[PDB]
Length: 48
Length: 42
Ligand SMILES: *[C@@H]1O[C@H](CO)[C@@H](O)[C@H](O)[C@H]1NC(C)=O
Image 1 (cartoon, chains in turn green, yellow):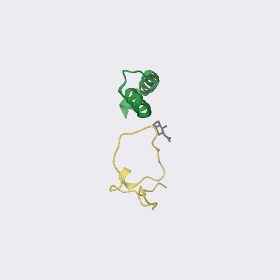
Image 2 (cartoon, helix red, strand yellow):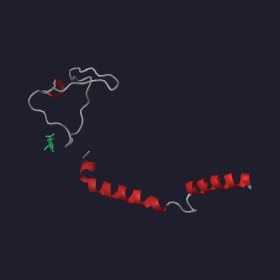
Image 3 (cartoon, chains in turn green, red):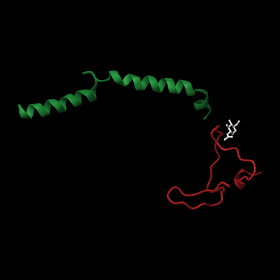
Image 4 (cartoon, chains in turn red, cyan):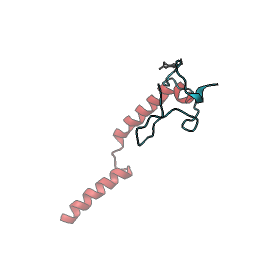
């Protein structure tokens, strides 16, 4: 409890930085976005 | 004043040592001075 009480502002700043960092995780290098695009491509390829 | 109840059924019971665990103080804890449960007595 003492660490969380002393480092509350650092915890909030780090959480805000991590939550704002996920805006740019939508590129081709990301694995989950690649899986999303693979699912969409499979859906299109069946019709093709 | 303050009673202990179960997490899945509402039944107010007296606060005992079986029901409670000692923890480090937190500023969001209630500082009670009139009626004190027996596990917090001396
Ligand atoms: C209980 O006492 C602590 C110690 O000063 C204080 O920080 C806290 O605000 C108090 N809480 C209440 C509900 O009075």
